[PDB]
Amino acid sequence: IQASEDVKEIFARARNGKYRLLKISIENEQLVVGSCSPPSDSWEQDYDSFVLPLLEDKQPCYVLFRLDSQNAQGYEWIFIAWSPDHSHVRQKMLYAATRATLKKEFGGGHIKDEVFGTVKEDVSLHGYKKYLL
Amino acid sequence: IQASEDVKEIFARARNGKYRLLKISIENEQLVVGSCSPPSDSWEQDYDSFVLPLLEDKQPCYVLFRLDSQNAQGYEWIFIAWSPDHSHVRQKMLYAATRATLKKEFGGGHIKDEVFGTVKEDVSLHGYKKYLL
């Protein structure tokens, strides 16, 4: 499973700062962009407004969220792996096994934090803050 | 000035109930889906939290918001035309001239209400309810 070049173009636009976040899903053995949004305010404000509405109750997905800070390679990102317990086991397995693949395709050096969650609280802004602790 | 089949496949998934909201933009003379959100709670509970954050201050867009009610053709939708005063004139013209086409591409029979707005107050849940009156 990999990201097509159409997807990698979106990845570049996102890391360029054009998007605040990207929702990535696995569809037919392919990593696809399921949603995206340009930045509006500071990252904290954008996190509250954009992250939670993307999470399905019985379907895993990944959410790459762009912070305002940068490292030697550009903006830093939060890699959110959403895997609800009400999800099908096959889907749970597929997303967990393909997570490292998406990371490589996106550029591991751009990932600052990696968060996992099975309930919305785990990946809410509060959840991220507690994770950082 | 038309929607691709890639977009129409998403329109079908949305109308099936998979999405509560679809944000549509015009990029490179083409209608594209930028952001989408699955349903969480009731349509009224989802409205402002899903819609408002996606409305850029200086960029027009279209938002297709799904209600919980259905007509003879399936779920009914609210078709929101967002065109801020601080948007470029070209953009305002482009979106206003393409609105009717989008309606046709999505299926006018699924659109229960059509709302226009240049400020958030015009298209918030309160604004929509006032419009209905």
Image (cartoon, coloured by chain):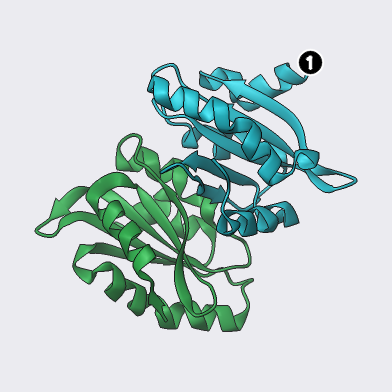
Chain colours: A green, B cyan
User: From the viewer's perspective, is residue B91 above or below residue A58?
Assistant: above
Name the residue located 41 percent from the left edge and 50 percent from the top edge: A126
Observer-nearest residue: B5 or A100?
B5
Observer-nearest residue: B33 or A45?
B33
Q: Where is residue A49 in the image (x, y as percent from the top left)?
A: 46, 41
User: From the viewer's perspective, is residue B70 above or below residue A28?
Assistant: above
Q: Mark 1 lies on which chain?
A: B
Q: In this view, does A124 lie to the left or right of B21?
A: left
Q: How crowded is mark 1: few (under 14 residues within 10 Å), some or many (20 or more)?
A: few
Badge 1 amino acid: Leu
- Number of labelled discs? 1
Name the residue located 35 percent from the left edge and 73 percent from the top edge: A102
Name the residue located 46 percent from the left edge and 50 percent from the top edge: A51
Name the residue located 43 percent from the left edge and 27 percent from the top edge: B91
Outermost right residue = B72
Which residue position holds label 1? B133
Q: Position of residue A104 (x, y in %)?
A: 28, 75
Quarter residue A33 falls in = bottom left
Quarter residue A115 falls in = bottom left
Quarter residue B9 falls in = bottom right
Q: Position of residue B68 (x, y in %)?
A: 78, 44
**Residue A126 in view, yes or no:** yes
Observer-nearest residue: A128 or A112?
A112
**Residue B87 in view, yes or no:** no
User: From the viewer's perspective, is residue B96 above or below residue A41?
Assistant: above
Q: Quadrant of the N terminus of chain A?
A: bottom left
Q: Where is residue A9 in the image (x, y as percent from the top left)?
A: 31, 60
Helix, strand or loop at disc 1? loop
